[PDB]
Length: 66
Image (cartoon, rainbow, N blue to C red; front, side):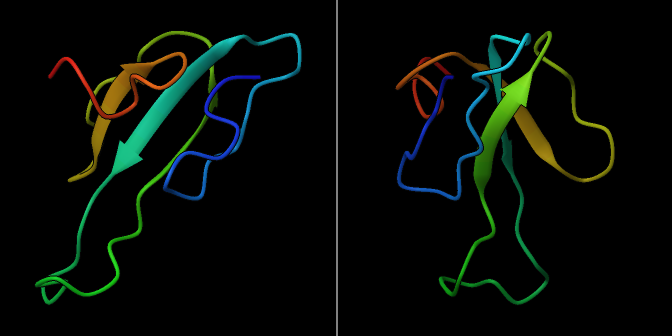
């Protein structure tokens, strides 16, 4: 599994899948409040479907190399 438990909710991908995606979005009033950012399992770095900021991660890179 990847991500395991970063400083977010995490999800881990210890199953057939081995990729770790990182979802990070905010609210219209999250001005330094409780952002809901969590990374989990995935197959291939996804894009930004709705107004969500996804990224490609596989370990402690969920928040690096922007």
